[PDB]
Amino acid sequence: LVANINGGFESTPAGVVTDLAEGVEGWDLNVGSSVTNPPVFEVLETSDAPEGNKVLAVTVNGVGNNPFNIQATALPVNVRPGVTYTYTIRARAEQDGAVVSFTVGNQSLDEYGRLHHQQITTEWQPFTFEFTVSDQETVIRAPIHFGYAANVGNTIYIDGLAIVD
Ligand SMILES: O[C@@H]1[C@@H](O)[C@H](O[C@@H]2CO[C@@H](O[C@@H]3CO[C@@H](O[C@@H]4CO[C@@H](O)[C@H](O)[C@H]4O)[C@H](O)[C@H]3O)[C@H](O)[C@H]2O)OC[C@H]1O
Ligand SMILES: [Ca+2]
Ligand SMILES: [Ca+2]
């Protein structure tokens, strides 16, 4: 049981994602206009996948002004007021030196919590944290920020987002 939808990209056909807002069920991908060299978002079928058969790959070619100018946001995330949740996701990168922040917030852009400038390695690792829905929201969001300068020239892979009571 999880709060989010399509946490492992298994719903989505393999291929480059061109419809960023609606091409991946359960997710909203977004690239801001300050990112002059846009990234490539791809759902990959690979036996490397920690969950199922598929992962999301984000190839970063350039950045903008804020880390969220390249982001993948899980939406909707169905929760209950006052409840504490565990967030877990798996991530790795093509090259050394990647940086990602894993966040959760409300539709008002208020963050309930995050894992900040996580050090992503060339091997799959789990990244986990707890957060509490400290207000009266029931439908929240989980933005992952990839727009760090250190990621230029890298591909970041994510899989198996699970937000659990
Ligand atoms: O989808 C996008 C949303 O993600 C975005 O939300 C804003 C994201 O930035 C937020 O502010 C961040 C909060 O984290 C600060 O870093 C802290 C440093 O200390 C660490 O201990 C702690 O874990 C970190 O949280 C960072 O300085 C600051 O910039 C902001 O509050 C959110 O509103 O909004 C735009 C959406 O498109
Ligand atoms: Ca998967
Ligand atoms: Ca969407």
Image (spheres, rainbow, N blue to C red):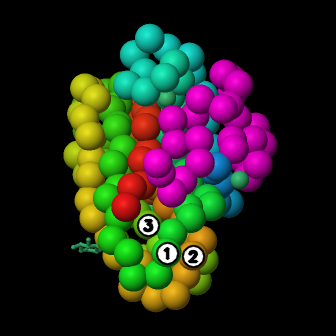
Earlier sequence position, callout 3 versus callout 2? 3
Q: Is residue 142 a member of the stretch shown in magenta?
A: no
Q: Which mark is residue 27?
A: none
Percent coordinates x, y for residue 141 in the rendering:
55, 65
Q: Quadrant of residue 115?
A: bottom left
The magenta stretch is 1-25
Residue occupying image coordinates x 44% and y 35%: 159
Earlier sequence position, callout 2 versus callout 1? 1
Q: Is residue 8 a member of the stretch shown in magenta?
A: yes
From the image, tell me which residue sits under label 1: 80
Q: Decide which of 73, 75 is in the foreground and name it.
A: 75
Residue sticking out furthest to the front: 1
Instruction: Calculate the distance from the C-alpha at mark 3 to the C-alpha at mark 2.
Output: 13 Å
Q: For mark 2, does the 10 Å Cα neighbourhood hold few (<14), some (14 to 19), or many (20 or more) residues? A: some
Instruction: Calculate the distance from the C-alpha at mark 1 to the C-alpha at mark 3.
Output: 14 Å
Q: How many marks?
A: 3
Residue sticking out furthest to the bottom: 135
Residue occupying image coordinates x 39% and y 55%: 164
Instruction: Calculate the distance from the C-alpha at mark 2 to the C-alpha at mark 1.
Output: 5 Å
Residue occupying image coordinates x 49% and y 14%: 46
Q: Which mark is residue 138?
A: 2
User: What is the three-letter code of the residue carrying label 2?
Assistant: Thr
Q: Decide which of 1, 127 is in the foreground and name it.
A: 1
Disc 3, SS: strand
From the image, tell me which residue sits under label 3: 104
Q: Decide which of 51, 33 is in the foreground and name it.
A: 51
User: What is the three-letter code of the residue carrying label 1?
Assistant: Arg
Q: Is mark 3 within 8 Å of ligand 1?
A: no
Earlier sequence position, callout 1 versus callout 3? 1
Disc 1, SS: loop
Percent coordinates x, y for residue 3 in the rendering:
51, 57
